[PDB]
Length: 49
Length: 50
Ligand SMILES: *[C@@H]1O[C@H](CO)[C@@H](O[C@@H]2O[C@H](CO)[C@@H](O)[C@H](O)[C@H]2NC(C)=O)[C@H](O)[C@H]1NC(C)=O
Image 1: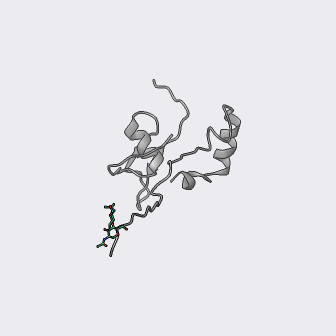
Image 2 (image 1 turned 45 degrees about the vertical axis):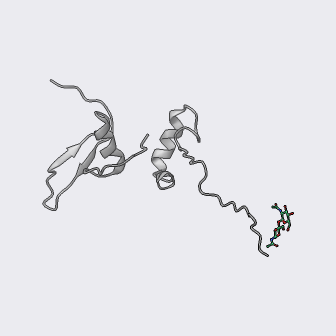
């Protein structure tokens, strides 16, 4: 005799995509923070890419 | 008589020394795209810039 049985299988596919910024997240509205990040250079443009 | 205001430009140089073309940063979305992608020719696609 033979019988048929079912089995579940769950694999994740993708997560929610998240994007951040250095201009707003690091400093709220102060232009001095922008001045220090611009004199220091590009540190998180590669992170954005 | 003209007026001058401070912003950033992007310039493309040549081996002879003389500049042959230039583009600004804030006049059009295409100009902002060229300013942020560090390139003149822009391929088709989605670009998160600012
Ligand atoms: C194989 O086994 C299944 C159960 O595991 C059998 O199905 C039942 O069979 C009995 C009698 O053999 C019936 O009274 C039940 O109503 C059946 N269950 C149902 C229809 O859900 C099946 O008959 C067996 N097959 C063989 C060839 O022996």
